[PDB]
Image 1 (tube, protein in one colour):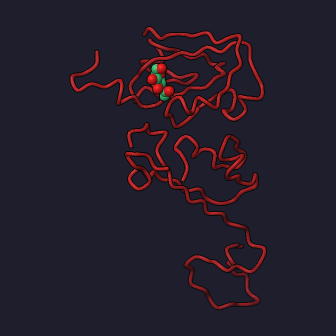
Image 2: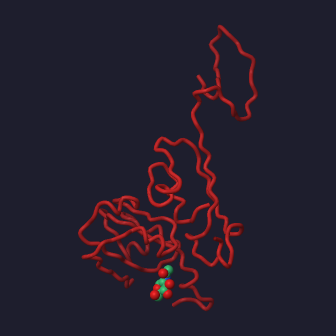
Image 3: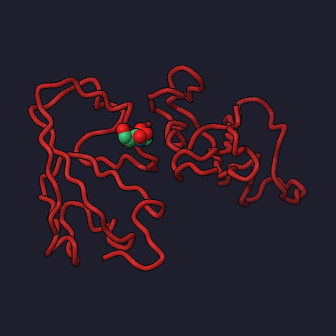
Length: 49
Length: 99
Length: 50
Ligand SMILES: *[C@@H]1O[C@H](CO)[C@@H](O)[C@H](O)[C@H]1NC(C)=O
């Protein structure tokens, strides 16, 4: 589960914060990336920590 | 029709805090890439800020006509830069209408 | 929940396929056909045609 600003970092040949320190994809990657919003399930009014 | 222009010069620019400042989706750049902005550098950076309708966000592009792009804000064909747009329904919307 | 649309949580599932070098263990729904020989036919062996 990532933030909405960093969905584009899950791609071959990307840098930033997730793609450098958390989850890096190879340059010759074949496959599919599926992302959907989960505001109803993964958020709290007091803050999901 | 009266968009502001701010000159950014004589400083060190960090482009990673732009994502923390505003909740936008795409850092849509044209002459450069958003991930390579922190390595190389420029002479001067100008920031233009305005509010439009969601129909006319696509008109902010080099080489395109319309209503905003012809009479309000025209971009050159040799435009090198990034366009950052995000929704403003919580600050720029009223039930009685905005004038 | 009061954040902007760019700060919302996003569930990400990445499916990572590898191209066929070993014998295939996962294959989609396709009914097999009895093998013929010594005839100019169209074949489909584990996803490659010809
Ligand atoms: C914008 O500036 C105001 C005034 O300094 C501050 O209260 C607010 O938290 C700032 N917004 C962000 C997202 O930092």
